[PDB]
Image (cartoon, rainbow over all chains, first blue to last red; front, side, top):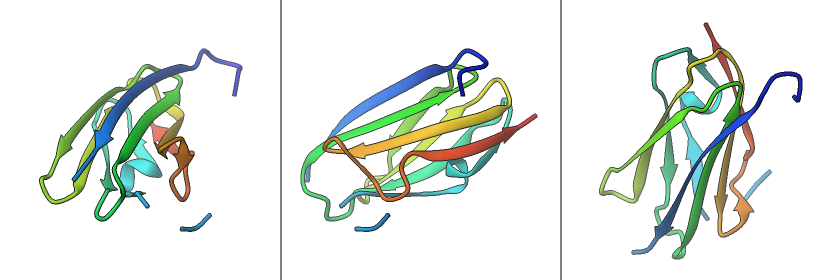
Length: 17
Length: 91
């Protein structure tokens, strides 16, 4: 980890009944 | 790592390059709260997420380079059991 570029994809959800 | 939201599915552990890798997020009788999904690895993987209507979410990501991807799943700032996961994505 760190030798090649690292990327992030993200998602946030509010969970509610 | 024990327990609340949970996560299971093939995409948590393995995948193949350019095909959608999938897993499930079970929110049956979770509180209400913030669900974070993140994926880190050698490429920016597109995430898609559908509510299955039954307290279950079907999540897929599309990895474009092979390698190791970390899948991070948090409920209200806390790691779900097994999170962060590591998927070996082969070519």
